[PDB]
Image: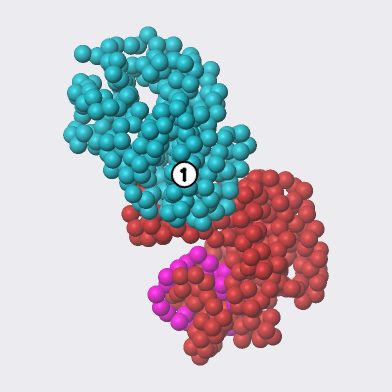
Chain colours: A red, B cyan
Amino acid sequence: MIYTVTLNPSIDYIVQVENFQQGVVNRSERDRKQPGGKGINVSRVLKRLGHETKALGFLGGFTGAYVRNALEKEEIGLSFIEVEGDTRINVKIKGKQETELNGTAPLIKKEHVQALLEQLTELEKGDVLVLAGSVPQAMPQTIYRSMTQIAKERGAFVAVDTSGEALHEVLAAKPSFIKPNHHELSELVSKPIASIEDAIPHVQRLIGEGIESILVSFAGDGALFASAEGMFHVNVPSGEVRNSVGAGDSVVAGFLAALQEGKSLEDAVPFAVAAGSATAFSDGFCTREEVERLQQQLQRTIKKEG
Amino acid sequence: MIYTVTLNPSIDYIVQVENFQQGVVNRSERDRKQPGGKGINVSRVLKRLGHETKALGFLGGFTGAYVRNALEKEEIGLSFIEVEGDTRINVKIKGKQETELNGTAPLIKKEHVQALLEQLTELEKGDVLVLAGSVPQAMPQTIYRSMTQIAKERGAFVAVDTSGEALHEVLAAKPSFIKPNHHELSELVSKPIASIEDAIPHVQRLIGEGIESILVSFAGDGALFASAEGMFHVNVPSGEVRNSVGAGDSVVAGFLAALQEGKSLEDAVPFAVAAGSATAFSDGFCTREEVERLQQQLQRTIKKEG
């Protein structure tokens, strides 16, 4: 049904140290590690929302074994291609400041990329393909455009959450749904967008260019959703954000979980934004209960637009 | 024959990064992962110098599995005790400002910190017990004092490489060898130090309390050795130090390797100081051939003390 692709998964090593300072021996007070990567995170959250997914991508070494074991324990569908190097270890330092340091991508022989593309020919009509995250530089940045084509030639629904050249490249493939935050969208059109008004003309050009739906977040300023069927705004429940290591991925899962449940593209927006917020407010990720709650609240702030 | 103890072992994650800012992101340019822990390093460097050893300590979690697999490949003797906790990960960032980030020590039950002491009971006359590295706050900072005893009461040679209360409390136990750098010595004799003479009176008193040998390195300026047979100085090879990760652990391994091969306490010093700077003048752990060479260099640099 729903397939997620994570080209560069990882072990997110989350560490809070209210004292983290350069050139010095920092100790940790609170340590945690969890499998990471945008595709993987959409899977995990989907699971928490009661939906299965089959996770795809590349995994290597003991760190990859850790990632595979974990998803296994969470009873999440998976079919990763083993690679030679080790899966990267990403370091997330919380506390006073918020500093990140990503590990190097592991080498991926061309045969593996060919095998990953091979798996996609398995998508059937009505399946969903989620391509989220960065594309290792060693790989053709047009990779998502390729995977989207394979998917579309099989009737599969494509949801994309990337940036840079990779996102620019995917457009010609006309995926079904994209979710750029306002900064990613500004980067895509090479123009600044700070308000809902700044984005509307561009969104309208994208829908007419074949993109079926788009959801642009403006952080604590709500979200804008456009479909050839319409355009409207929605607010965020507001609250103290206790975490921010997979909130955009939650929005994607929420949207897709709702679509699975038969709701309409428009009707799904409320649930997705809430899922993002729920995760943004809890130490870990959102729960089916939390989302439903917040969603009820947001399902009114719905202001038309366009 | 030579036992090493590592209470808080770990996987050392070295990541080279330039212009390693803060608050934002940071992409590694080069990564590296290997077993960490002072005792562990001593066993690894001893292996390279041609000598076996059995490493003891506490490992847990997939991280602990890694440590164990790696040492088993280097064919290093071992017998750690599995604790329900997850061996830590210390992120050693390098560049123009090598920083560090030590992970939260796992969790060790009493019966564990007891089956260990229980292992020491096998020690025999002529054996060697190496105690190095800080102590997990989850344990009493007197733990080395306690082990030295068991060890000493068995004709075993105890060498210690620590600092802080831990180092302070071991003294009354009368260990056979300690290597406080000129600083740790100030942090011990609770008094500042500087001259090569500003330490002899104090290294003298320590020897008089029952401690067999003391090796105190003046960072960049040489090192002083003291035993009941008198003392002498030796200068450091002098060269470009690329790595520091495990230099002190090398002087210790060198000193022990040299005594294993029959050489005397004082005659083993050159060899130990050689292993130290041979590891430092490199991007990895020193090789036998390297030590022997610089050994001769330092061999001539020998001056008795007044």
Magenta part of the protein: which range? A229-255
Q: Horizontally, is B225 left or right of A282 in the view?
A: left
Q: Nearer the viewer, residue A185 or B159?
A: B159
Q: Give the image quarter of residue B157.
A: top left
- Residue pictured at 57% horizontal, 52% vertical: B62
Label 1 amino acid?
Glu
Residue A265: percent from the left, percent from the top? Answer: 65, 82
Give the left or right position of residue B259, taking residue A146 as reference: left
Q: Position of residue A15 (x, y in %)?
A: 44, 57
Residue A213 at least partly seen: no
Query: Where does label 1 land, which residue?
Result: B118
- Quarter of the rendering occupied by the C terminus of chain A: bottom right
Above or below residue A119? Residue A174 is below
Give the camera-side residue of A170 and A59.
Answer: A59
Q: Quadrant of residue B169?
A: top left
Find numbered disc 1 in the image and state the secondary structure of the residue it sits on: helix
| Label 1 crowd (10 A; few <14 / some 14-19 / many >=20) | few
Q: Quadrant of the N terminus of chain A?
A: bottom right
